[PDB]
Image (cartoon, one colour):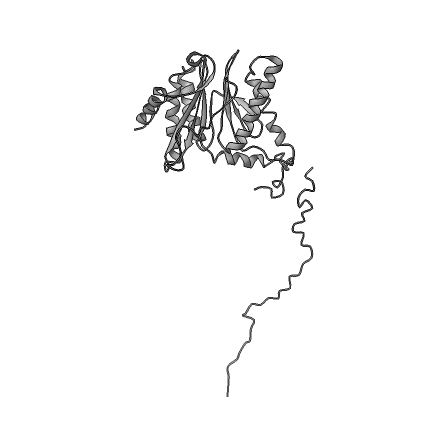
Length: 38
Length: 246
């Protein structure tokens, strides 16, 4: 009744994103006004 | 903006031994009018582009030169008040050099009582430096003098000076003269030879009209004091100048 094949391949890309990280050192100011400047 | 941390304050040093707030003040002088001073065989002549923003301003009485005690002058290019704050220290201490020594203050000893003061602002933290670069010279016992003041605290002795936005230009026409005339200009051609320059230095601002000002100090024509100009002397110098460039 049917002679064709299908050949289900992985022609599609894909991805899994949980790029979870730790540090975040971005920007500590301990001199918000330099604390008497002097 | 090499350092986003080392600019919020003064009295710091970058990793490259620099302090950048001085290196940003200097960019406030550049956004200022032009001002020069020529050295001569007897004295000096100063000058300036005095811009006019409207038609409504009175002529010849929004002057910009400030005259210190009769024998030295100071002209600005930058932020004016920090300037006028500065002569108004130079106009008082020189007295305090007189009432102890009785001589009019010389020119160098007037500098080190400025060039040492300005340097004080660029080492504390609770202050701001000056956004000026003022020229000053005059006459004394041992000849003429002429100097530049610069917000880093430096000053050096110049035959010719120019600041503002017309720096790169007037640093040429003052190189030409010092090749033609090593023997010292007289004090009645330098003047008109100054007017030639400010009319050439304007052309960064060909938009807007303006006004020209001069002040001049030399022994022969004045007997050794500071003074403005008036009359045929500057009017011809105007007539001299815009002639040659048309």
